[PDB]
Length: 146
Ligand SMILES: O=C(Oc1ccc(CO)cc1)c1ccc([N+](=O)[O-])s1
Ligand SMILES: [Mn+2]
Ligand SMILES: [Mn+2]
Ligand SMILES: [Zn+2]
Ligand SMILES: [Zn+2]
Image (cartoon, rainbow, N blue to C red; front, top):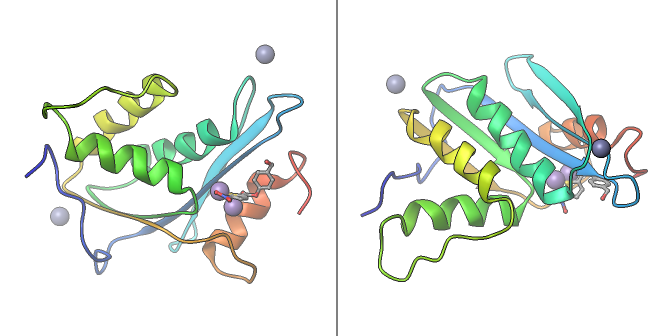
């Protein structure tokens, strides 16, 4: 019983957003974006950012640009946990909100509860030709070598 329930399995039929972000610590330059299984993609370049911010920013773009039912695959355990924990503990007993990234996370949650159904799952970064590998390349170009 929370302020929303994420889906326990992928939403059959819904479009899938493979999100990723990448940042460079020395310059605080970074990129966030997505590729989808309906031939959609988007990459944005960011300044003054961090790796965790860019993974969160990517999810925000995916929620922003999608319909009411959406599948999101991320490789960030941080991004998944912080969003899931926020949903499960909202208005609950021992909730101290995070300090870091709190503005972006609040922005994401706001987008999130507007949705009808959201499936959000983690996969380890891996090589190959699937979705996570494609967006990883896009957000990595000029930010870090792979
Ligand atoms: O997109 C990715 O490639 C890069 C490459 C370089 C940098 C620079 O730090 C950041 C991301 C991801 C790698 C690892 C991820 N993961 O959640 O472990 S996403
Ligand atoms: Mn990543
Ligand atoms: Mn990646
Ligand atoms: Zn700057
Ligand atoms: Zn629907």
